[PDB]
Amino acid sequence: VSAISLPTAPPAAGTESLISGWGNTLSSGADYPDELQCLDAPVLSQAECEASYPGKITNNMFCVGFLEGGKDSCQGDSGGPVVSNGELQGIVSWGYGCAQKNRPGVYTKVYNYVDWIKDTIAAN
Amino acid sequence: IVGGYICEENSVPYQVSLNSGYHFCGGSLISEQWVVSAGHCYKSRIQVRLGEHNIEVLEGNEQFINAAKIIRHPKYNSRTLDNDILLIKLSSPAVINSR
Ligand SMILES: [Ca+2]
Image (tube, rainbow over all chains, first blue to last red; front, side, top):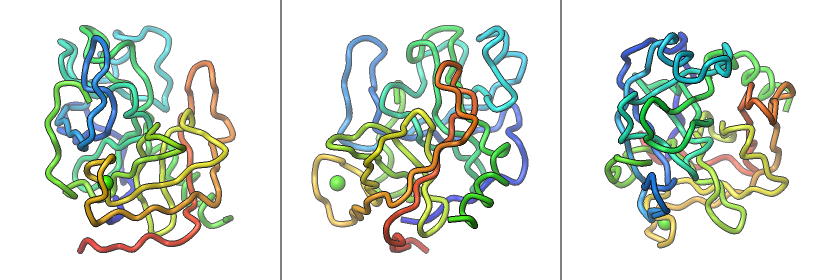
C-alpha cells in the first residue's frame, strides 16, 4: 500500500497507461473477477475522443484505450486509476459499452483538479 | 477490465476497492489519509479496502478503513458526468507498507 502522485501535466496522446480494477471482464454478460485486473492502454488524441463521443467530451474528460475495442474498462471499474510515469492521470468515468468498436473509455482529467484536491485536503 | 491480465499481487499498491456491502467502485490512494475516486461512486457510507488482490479471500495485506468524509466535486453533473471526481478522507491514516 502506497500513494500515487498527482499529475504535473495534463495527459498526452500516445502515453502508455496502466488501468486497473475489479470490474466486469466481459463485453457480453458478466464475469466479475476475484483478482485485480490490469490493462495497458494508450491515451487517445483529443480529436479521436471528440470524434468518438460528439458533443459529450468536456475539458475535464479524456479518452484512453483502443478504437478497435477489445480492451477497455467496464462496470465496476468506475473510480479506479489510470497511471503513467508514477502519476495519476485519469479516473475511470464512463463509456458506451465495454471494449466496443469506436467507443473507448472516457476518464476524468485529474490534472484539472490538482488545486481542488489540495484545497479540499487543507480545509478538511 | 475487459481484455486485460491479472495484476501481479500488490503490484498496484495505490489501488483501492470501495465496498458498501459489496465491491462497487475503485479508487486511488493519494496520501496517507485521502483517496480519489469518481463522483458517480458517491455513497453515504463507504469502506475503503486497501492492500487487496483477491477481494473475496483474506490473504494477509488488507487494510479495511471506513470513510470519515466523502466529498464530491461541487460542480459534479449527474447527467453529463462532468467533474466526475470525489475525495474520501479515511477515518484513520493508511499504513504505508510499500517502499
Ligand atoms: Ca483479499
